[PDB]
Image (cartoon, rainbow, N blue to C red; front, top):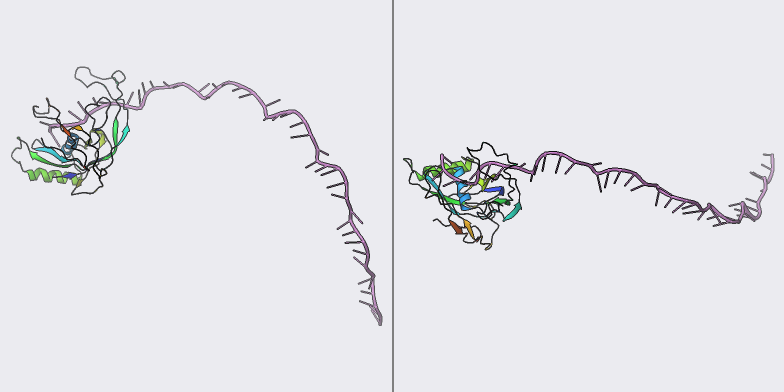
Length: 205
RNA sequence: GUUGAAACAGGGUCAGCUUGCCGUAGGUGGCAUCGCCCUCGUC
């Protein structure tokens, strides 16, 4: 288990419902929490698994309308001209977040030869303490960086001390099981937070 | 290296135009510097 300690000035774990008008999930999504732990280290042998988020700064919001673009980019049309494809996505962002994601991982079917769980474990451990990553972890949106740390047990004060808000059914981790290589056909599994007692435990599927 | 990506607040718009702080009003009226005091005493 790794008690990595994602933190950042802003964060947007955009609720699936309020995607066009981004309203962040009140805490780190276990998908966004996990994909962060793939940004620091991943390989198609490691399969990350968030075991317990722990909120470390209170759920505080700042709305940010960004002139986002409306349409994907495409081989077909060789430019956007944003002023033609403009959209103004509001973003109820999570200001001053922090999350100590108690996450571990497993070995996939394609673990390869060097399937050593300890190898990837210490690889990620060195990456996180050193600060290395494949990708500066995205707090839900890459516009938001995860000023992370690989805590050992506990090195920050979690604010939802007494029993606190149950954020309801949050996106857990989009189901890339039916997908071929590179996540084509997925689905969304979702979870009762369970509550936020003081740091939400997640459910392994 | 399979997992939210890409994304503007843009582009720009004199707060201007202009309008007496004025007209006008005694500082007056009035009040003793007074009352008084050997330059002496003397060589």
